[PDB]
Image (cartoon, rainbow, N blue to C red; front, top):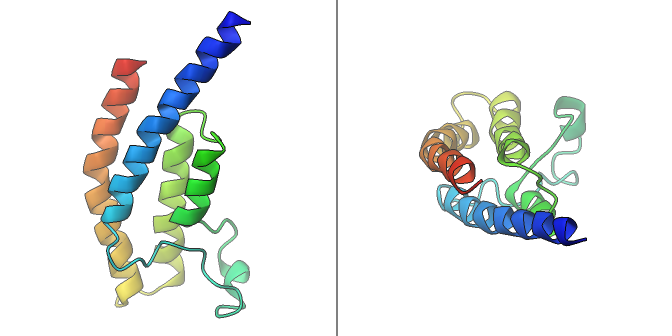
Length: 121
């Protein structure tokens, strides 16, 4: 149908905007602490601590499969990255500190993304 196509163009455009959002958030992690999944070879107990691991590469795979239906789902995954880190790592670690900085800087980007998603529909 023509409606299914319209719908699909909206999703494509959301994917376009979420791709730009993802790029902006990922620039706030210049150390690349959150770039890839925590290695289960190197942290073999990780899944005993963290039940839903997340990282920017895994978000990118979902994004490119047009797997985010709305901004809320994308924010859910971004918040997992931060929240997983702040639980596994102690306050006095470079990892924890990196997550706080990513959260704080990401807020600005996500605030305007929400306005853009609502505005452009």
